[PDB]
Length: 146
Length: 19
Ligand SMILES: [Ca+2]
Ligand SMILES: [Ca+2]
Ligand SMILES: [Ca+2]
Ligand SMILES: [Ca+2]
Image 1: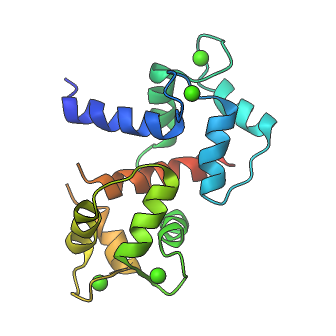
Image 2 (image 1 turned 30 degrees about the horizontal axis):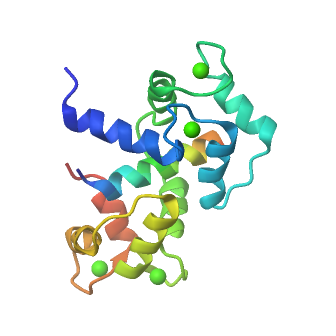
């Protein structure tokens, strides 16, 4: 039994890739997201990613195929170097602390804008030690929570 | 929602895609 919140989460994830809202993720759009995160896949490499889950053979990724992609490639858990890779995405200035301002920017860059109230809520929930920023240990620890 | 935990997972997704 899927909840509507689960469905909403899948939709948001899908829409991050599907920037033109046409219902399919193309190599261009997959590429755009991975380039926003510092990666440089080739067009062929992006096509290969699509091919793996491209069950109807049309060359692009639709909603159910994207679910399959996440099932396979969100296969459990952030190891260590990948958690650390993610931290680096958010800690833009490399100083070891994610500021509210940093988080807001990175999130806008990905393509999900949220009220500064929301961003501050994210910082505040994760900020265990009280300094108003999120260090690596706190970034790691927020990932365990409900 | 836990939007931030969700976005970290998506970032990890792209790491795992770019082999
Ligand atoms: Ca599209
Ligand atoms: Ca397809
Ligand atoms: Ca920083
Ligand atoms: Ca802190």
